[PDB]
Length: 18
Length: 124
Image (cartoon, rainbow over all chains, first blue to last red; front, top):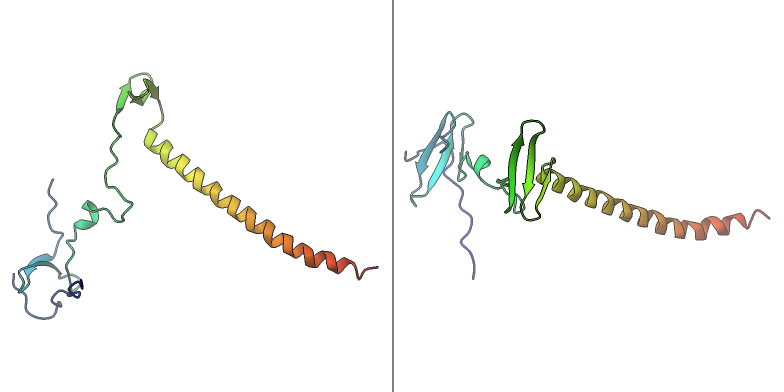
């Protein structure tokens, strides 16, 4: 089949759940 | 031992709930655990482990020093068999290479001859 497309991680500048 | 995150990194979660790594020093983010560089093969041909293979043993003789026992073949030797492997692996390739160079060198020559020979004829 077709694999899910590549996903980058949240960029540095911006909000993060830590 | 379990490695700890290097100085000034942070874990975070995606909406997905997947873990990613924040590198504050460089103001960058990553899916890749930074300590993966030490614990993961860096190539589909890499092994992190340098274990002696089944049947081999490290040994120390006070007179002679470190040596190696091969119980597969009831043998002992001085040289680390791992090292000699890598050596004669390399020596194999390093001259397999040199014959290919010898081959081209000749075949390039065998056609340079057809020209160079036709050249001397004018000198008559």
